[PDB]
Image 1 (cartoon, rainbow over the protein chains, first blue to last red):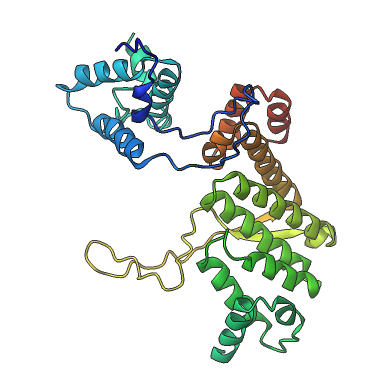
Image 2 (image 1 turned 180 degrees about the vertical axis):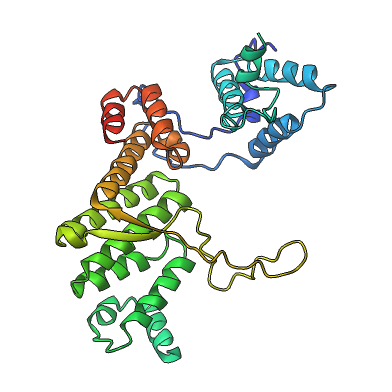
Length: 112
Length: 205
């Protein structure tokens, strides 16, 4: 919920799906294309995704509070935004199956 | 046919690709093409150059139509299987090579034949898809055949080129861009701020 020492330790729960094209730190001469994310970070990001899949009504509030804690920090917030955006995109053409994830931007703003 | 299969395999493993292209193959031409196509279908697209070999093999015999078809199949499979910056670059090059081959053909014959998107290419040697009851599902006996004209190939080329421009601007987007429809691609280009490429894509589609 708070990162007073800017340690960014919440990043271990997030796996980048796209390389951020930030062209603005031209200043360290170590070309290393494509490290696979560490096996630890893959397991923790799989845990966050697994906890969203078929979420029971009893775990809804705890899961949103977990995501709120994991969304503290600039990169963490952007990955959480991308996760909630990805959860909405899978059903625009069949209006008669209420099969959208309850943890999505579409569900939050449509409910409001 | 079994000796021909062995010859094609051993020459491909020895990298003696010139001899394989120059041989006359009197009456065996369709079988060589079928063997190399079957291997090009079975092998990984990034490790072995069998599509580039099939293309060289058809260009040498002035078969520009089949050369275009093979490079188009290569570009389609790269878009499905290889969602990397290098895969997208090879896909744009294969569609460009296809367009160049069809421009060498008279306009009346400048069309490629595709099985419709959703024709299960059963991998030759996949166990028959059994239903829950263990019966062989009857092969759906209509592979609907789509005829692609030069204008539809130009749309697919522009779509692959726009996917590559987005992936070059942001390497993290290469996985998403590889599957994006023309409409989703407009939304992604607009998020990146590549408005002229989005306008060009809106005009083409």
